[PDB]
Image (cartoon, rainbow, N blue to C red; front, side, top):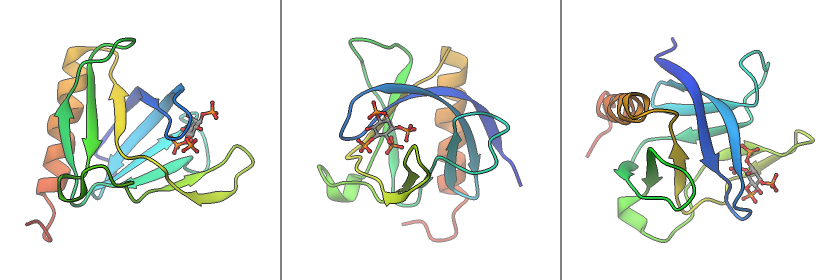
Length: 123
Ligand SMILES: O=P(O)(O)O[C@H]1[C@H](O)[C@@H](OP(=O)(O)O)[C@H](OP(=O)(O)O)[C@@H](OP(=O)(O)O)[C@H]1O
């Protein structure tokens, strides 16, 4: 079931704060928890119909983003839980994330392209 896991830094949506989060990529779904032993996902991002792209950030290096080619400037459909556990839809136009190192950043990038590609509903 698992495919790839490791820590990453992601920028919030409405509020632009980076949070260190544990990520798990599986079945073309990208999971992130606050801790590796967390029992439930803090957020879930369905990667279908999305694309990654290298970016340059003025605060964190080794970045890349997830955005929707088809609907530029439109909020990406995701599921997230608030601090208290309340379930809400995500509010990201793009998901910017900085890896700890280039090998990881690129390993994720490829690995995320691998899962999107291993999708029988690709266009
Ligand atoms: O705690 P503050 O400083 O308010 O910032 C939060 C965190 O960055 C959240 O990340 P995480 O959920 O990983 O803890 C993020 O939710 P997501 O990035 O998951 O959507 C929120 O986006 P908004 O709820 O859109 O503001 C953002 O407001």
